[PDB]
Amino acid sequence: VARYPPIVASMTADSKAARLRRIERWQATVHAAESVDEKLRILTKMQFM
Amino acid sequence: AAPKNRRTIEVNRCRRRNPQKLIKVKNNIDVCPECGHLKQKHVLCAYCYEKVCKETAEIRRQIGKQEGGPFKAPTIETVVLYTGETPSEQDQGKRIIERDRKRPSWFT
Amino acid sequence: ARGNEYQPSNIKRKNKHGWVRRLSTPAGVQVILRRMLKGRKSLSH
Amino acid sequence: ISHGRVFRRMGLGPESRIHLLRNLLTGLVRHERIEAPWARVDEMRGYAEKLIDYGKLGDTNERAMRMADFWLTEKDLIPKLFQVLAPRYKDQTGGYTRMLQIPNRSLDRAKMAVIEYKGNCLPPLPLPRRDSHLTLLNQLLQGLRQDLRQSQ
RNA sequence: CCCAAUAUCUACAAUCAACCAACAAGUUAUUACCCUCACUGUCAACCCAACCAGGCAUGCUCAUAAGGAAAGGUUAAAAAAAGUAAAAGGAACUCGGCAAAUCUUACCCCGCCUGUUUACCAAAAACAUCACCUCUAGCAUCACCAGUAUUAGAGGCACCGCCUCCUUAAAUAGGCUCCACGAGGGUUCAGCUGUCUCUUACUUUUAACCAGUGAAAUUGACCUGCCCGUGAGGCGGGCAUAACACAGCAA
Ligand SMILES: [Mg+2]
Ligand SMILES: [Mg+2]
Ligand SMILES: [Mg+2]
Ligand SMILES: [Mg+2]
Ligand SMILES: [Mg+2]
Ligand SMILES: [Mg+2]
Ligand SMILES: [Mg+2]
Ligand SMILES: [Mg+2]
Ligand SMILES: [Mg+2]
Ligand SMILES: [Mg+2]
Ligand SMILES: [Mg+2]
Ligand SMILES: [Zn+2]
């Protein structure tokens, strides 16, 4: 009956693994979006070069 | 406020060279009786500690090269073995971190 | 708060201190000639 | 006045103090030996000891699991705590960590300290031995050992 | 970084532009030419503030996929700064409920209202302002104005309507009509609270110590005491008096 917390990296930390996990956070924000409108909104709202 | 008069070199010398401001001679230095380097009593021989940190760093570099990436703290003990040292009968089931130089005399 | 009265602008700088503005009036030609006499190597802005 | 206050003051407040000590303790559990400023290590030694105490209770206990969840930040170390450290000290009932002072830091000349968990694999710290038992004063004291033992 | 010439035109808004409703009223026909991509910006941690918790227009992300580090090490003295908590009492503080905590009420003076002002001590009871009144002016192509007496300029006043003893235990305080509004001024009810009776604890910065880097006002010379008198560390008469840092205080 071992409740081991998961083996994941941290969210708020300033490293590379934290950056990847925040990438997964917004990608899971789009996976859990039902309208194609919102999927395209979230998947293109950040304007970069 | 502000000074009313310059202070002479005499007063400044009686302040700057007062004993309370001098650097005290340290009564607790000696020589590592075996190793023969300077040290304070309550502190580690600096040369010995450096020669230990070098080996710790080399061992840890091997550990990193073997564990691959981050988040890989093993769940078993670890033993480090130098050249021509077969894993002893007590160290089976413990991760081995091979090194390629003769074991230091100070490593027991 | 003061001290930032110079908000640079190339159009303004070339319009109100430039070669053509000096040469568009006798006073400006006098200015250019003074600065030619004193030896300057920056006659006009 | 600060009579009977056992906790140092460090960081930007109490919370930052707990977080600093938490990072030190995580580094200690991950590498089993760390060099840090002396006062911070002296503050963290008690926490490392009690962490091993909580880890002895074992995985099944939930209070210990929550505590080790808070006090370890990269969770790969929580296995270790409950399967390499706490088992290692099944015999010792106290004093799992040794703390030494080392040459002051080059840059800011702070008072340093190496702290490690007893029994690790690393090359051993150059501990200071006592005087050999065969020295003059020790020999005279050994003679007194004998002569007092026979009398009693 | 532009455009071949000439004539013609060019009455009706924009507001999801359709319903209602308004006022501040918002290019081509002919003639000439069958030519092709040259030239410049493109960097950065950046610019104006002597180096900087300041200043800096627009588009998009609205809490971050981007960007960063509030603690050189230590100890936990005073005084100072910011914050959190507080017994009973709740303005007795004080010039004044300034600050803080809590959210209610009532009136009075001034000004009608929104607005504007003394960049850097005054935001107001001052300026402006609709409304009213007075004075001047019969009119062309550079303002008033491509206007014309219901117009233009210059002044005063300030819509509109009406006319030309109580309070407190105690009190020097408060008590032309005219809604609405005010970081305006004065007063009051109730609450609230460390404002206070009367302070206390903890945290952070400062602080003190170790290490690095390292100013400025000020300075006749100083081997820089106290009391009484004279007119005051320095004169006189008494007293005191081994030298030397460090942290405080402000006669
Ligand atoms: Mg670019
Ligand atoms: Mg980032
Ligand atoms: Mg600190
Ligand atoms: Mg910092
Ligand atoms: Mg500091
Ligand atoms: Mg109270
Ligand atoms: Mg106003
Ligand atoms: Mg006002
Ligand atoms: Mg210093
Ligand atoms: Mg006197
Ligand atoms: Mg002093
Ligand atoms: Zn040694």
Image (spheres, helix red, strand yellow):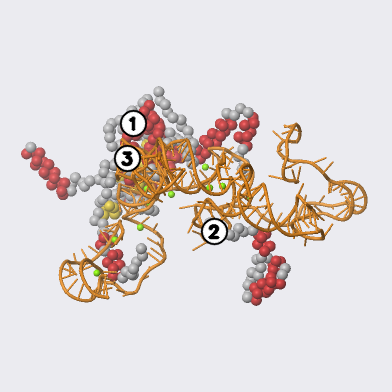
Q: Disc 3 marks which residue?
A: D45
In this view, the residue in front, B42 or A20, is: A20
Going 6% across and 39% down the picture, which residue do you hit? D151
Residue furthest to the top? A1
Q: Classify mark 3: residues with Cα within 10 Å, few (<14), some (14-19) or many (20+).
A: many
Label 1 vs label 3: CA separation?
14 Å
Along the horizontal axis of the image, is A31 left or right of C23?
A: left
Which kind of residue does numbered mark 2 sit on? Answer: Arg
Q: Quadrant of residue E91?
A: top left
How many numbered callouts?
Answer: 3
Given residues A2 and E16, the one toward you in this image is E16
Does any portion of residue A41 appear in the rendered image? yes
In the image, is residue A49 above or below residue E103? below
SS at mark 3 in the image: helix
Residue labelled with disc 1: D54
Mark sitting on residue D104: none
**Whether marks 1 and 3 lie on the same chain:** yes
Place of residue E21 in the rendered image (x, y in percent of width and height, measured from the top left): 73, 36
Residue E10 to residue D77: above or below: below
Along the polypeptide, which appears first: circle 1 or circle 3? 3
Q: Chain of mark 1?
A: D
Q: Residue at 14%, 44% (x, y): give it.
A: D142
Horizontal and vertical percent position of residue C45 = 65, 66
Question: Which residue carries the number 2 mark?
Answer: C2
Q: CA distance from mark 1 to mark 2?
A: 63 Å
Looking at this view, is E166 or D142 the one in front?
E166
Q: Residues within 10 Å of mark 1 (few under 14, many from 20)?
A: many
**Mark whose residue sits in front, 3 or 2:** 2
Q: Amino acid at mark 3?
A: Arg
Q: Position of residue E32 (x, y in %)?
A: 91, 54
Image quadrant occupied by the N terminus of chain B: bottom left
Give the residue at x 59% y 60%.
Answer: C6
